[PDB]
Each structure stands twice: as structure tokens, then as C-alpha cells.
Image 1 (cartoon, helix red, strand yellow):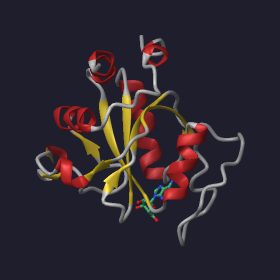
Image 2 (cartoon, helix red, strand yellow; image 1 turned 180 degrees about the horizontal axis):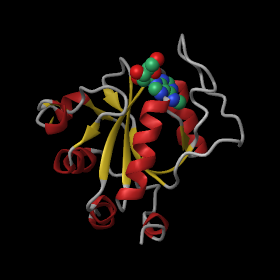
Image 3 (tube, protein in one colour; image 1 turned 45 degrees about the vertical axis):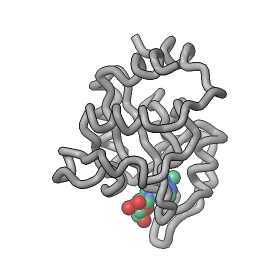
Image 4 (tube, helix red, strand yellow; image 1 turned 180 degrees about the vertical axis):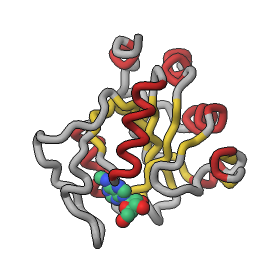
Length: 165
Ligand SMILES: CNc1ncnc2c1ncn2[C@@H]1O[C@H](CO)[C@@H](O)[C@H]1O
């Protein structure tokens, strides 16, 4: 069903993540971690303290799809297992040095063709697929986008809920 999912998303904040490659999203799905550039890292840390849930919605560039969504379980932390990210041209490992822990809510894909009716007020009412890495998605648009994803029957939101309050 969708009731625990709606509960997790209630009063959540949503951010679009644009990965330049599939490799890093696969790593994030396997290891439960994400890193972003310093400008976005600061925004996510602020959001983590402000809301009951912060949701990252992932899209690999040129894939025409979202690859899933996850909830931040921590602020960014440096000084751990150095993650073997595939680095785009012009990006350091120190730039991706902040590592957020994430709990996946849905690891299934959603094609952009299925979200064409959703626009994001925080990005000039452009279709929600459009946005730079880190673009915040307004609550109602983000909730509806997350609810469009196919259910992921492999995930039990019980332990995710157990970390909220
Ligand atoms: C692990 N983290 C990441 N992996 C791959 N691409 C990323 C990324 N974080 C940001 N990017 C993208 O890299 C671009 C800059 O080269 C940004 O505009 C994002 O779209």
C-alpha cells in the first residue's frame, strides 16, 4: 500500500539530484550514500535539520528517467570510507568529500514521460524533470512525483519511520 509512504513524505522537503553517470547512482543504491558539490551540500544539511524528512529524487543525465528516491538519514560527514565515485571532468574527490547517509524508499525507475503533468513552482513552473542538481521541489509537486513511482516491494518503511520522530 501507500499509507506508510505518505506518512514518510508528510511535511517532507524534496530535492532533485542530477547524476552525470549511472555508476554513481548504482553505488548509492548499494551503499546507501550520496555526495554532491559544496553548494548543494550546505543546502541539504540545512534542510535535514528543518524537516521531518528530506527526500532526494535521483535522475541520471540523458537517461530520460528518474532512478528512484531516498531519505537523508544524516547530515554530511567527512573522514570515512572514501567512496569510489566516477568523477565527471573537472570534479575533485575533495569536492564530493561530504558523504550523506541515505535510506532508499524506491529503487525503481520512472520515465520523464510519466511526470509531464507535474511542474515545480520553485523552478518557474517548469516540468519537474527540469532542474539543476540540488533544485528544491515544492511539497505538493514532490509528493505527487514520489507517488508516481512504481511501488518497491523490497523495502519496508517501518525502520525508516522508526528514525523520524
Ligand atoms: C556522487 N555525486 C555526483 N555524481 C555524478 N554527478 C554529479 C554528482 N553530483 C553532482 N553531479 C553532477 O555534476 C555536475 C557538475 O559536473 C552537476 O551539475 C551535477 O549534475
